[PDB]
Image (cartoon, rainbow, N blue to C red):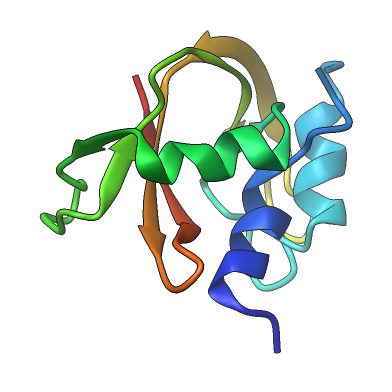
Length: 122
């Protein structure tokens, strides 16, 4: 099906938004992150695809899993953190929408060298 690069865009990119308390509940479902099970946590980046792809040539840092192909953004980025609530019961996945401006860390692979995993936000 979709490529790893495509999967990263589907799960983590949302350039349209620069949202509401309903954001995560709507996005987690629309992006198919609650099809099999309620994905515990997920982050959406509100920056252009170009700016995010550019992170692959920025600050090289260690990935949480120990791999060395992670990169941290030199500048902060608008992001939205989605964290599953306690009352949330599949298929009705409920999330807590939390906006913030932090540096993101993504794992990059391939040719072209592009983001394939969202590792963290600091």
